[PDB]
Length: 83
Length: 83
Ligand SMILES: [Cl-]
Image (tube, rainbow over all chains, first blue to last red; front, side, top):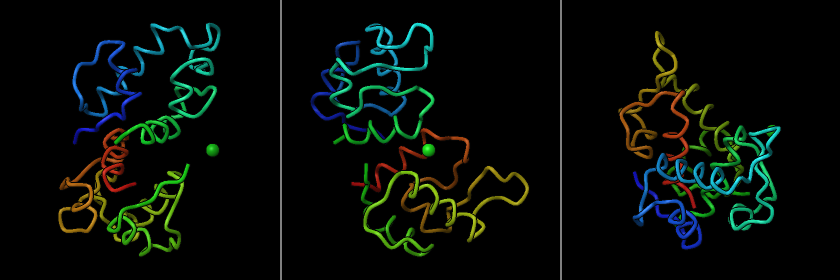
């Protein structure tokens, strides 16, 4: 099973090194984690909290922040950005 | 965020009490639990394994079995049966 990111999440994925149109969900998480890392969107002191409120990811996901421990919310926010 | 099961997952969900045409991921997972557990698709001896080769569920997931601890696979198999 491969998934097809909608266009804006595609651009987001490519900006940290993804190359195709379709990905396993594992590839999508990998690039999501790279993106949050390289952009430093996490709290320094509570590293599992992501502030994405000023960022394209907050727009795509629909939320101004979340924690990486909210797996179900993260999967749901991803679904919205899949064709 | 409301998801909308395609017709087969809907059938599965209805058969274990769901009424709506739309659900939270929270609910979708609950009913699915209900489904597996009320038909005893899981192995008695190693209970994290669900065997669905002889069941409606194997047809919608596309696997002969899966393990409840494989969350990424579960969400992925679920997205293909959603809008
Ligand atoms: Cl909750």
